[PDB]
Amino acid sequence: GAYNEAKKAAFKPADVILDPKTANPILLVSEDQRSVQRAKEPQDLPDNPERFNWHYCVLGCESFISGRHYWEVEVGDRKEWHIGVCSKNVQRKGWVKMTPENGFWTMGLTDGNKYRTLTEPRTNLKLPKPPKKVGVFLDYETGDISFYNAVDGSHIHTFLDVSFSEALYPVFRILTLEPTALTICP
């Protein structure tokens, strides 16, 4: 409603571009670097330090170190996805649990209709109607990372008062093979 729109007025629209050097080798980044798909099996890519080698993750190219920013992700009719923000300084090699304590502030969908935070423990989110487009808001100085349905402005989750000192990236994760990609709205 009017509340989420005038919120949007106070946050700078970020132009998020996926970074192919960060993407786990099971992921494909599109030619326009706005969408991500999965491959049936891993591609042959370098194990460069930037790359997630266990988690099925990819980062934006640009990080945030101050200010208020937002971007929007077309999740569409996908059955599975997770999105949010992570530290520049997360562990990219080997497994770490994707939780706030490890520098991941994410939420998403599993099995078509189970929305959750990747808080520790996870928290189940009851969304009266499924989002097609998710708005992600970052306020670096307050420490808030929030998720909204970008069409009706309805709130999905906020991580409040996080203690940020680090650069933060947009992060995206997909586990499934589906016909619909995960796509950044410009």
Image: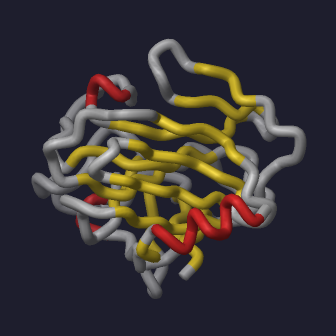
**Rendered view: 151 above or below 175:** below
Residue depicted at x 41% and y 55%? 138
- Give the x, y percent position of residue 122: 55, 19
Check the image and name the residue furthest to the right.
Answer: 128
Residue 160: in sight, yes or no? yes
In depth, the one of 186 and 174 nearer the eye is 186
- Give the x, y percent position of residue 25: 35, 56
Q: Would residue 108 be found to the left or right of residue 41 on screen?
A: right
In depth, the one of 114 and 64 nearer the eye is 64
- Say which quadrant the N terminus sits in: bottom right
- Give the x, y percent position of residue 80: 67, 44
- Give the x, y percent position of residue 112: 79, 40
Residue depicted at x 23% and y 31%? 94
Residue depicted at x 88% and y 39%? 128
Q: Would residue 138 be found to the left or right of residue 117 on screen?
A: left
Residue depicted at x 53% and y 38%? 158
In depth, the one of 74 and 147 nearer the eye is 147
- Say which quadrant the C terminus sits in: bottom right
Q: Would residue 99 be found to the left or right of residue 150 on screen?
A: left
Check the image and name the residue furthest to the left.
Answer: 49
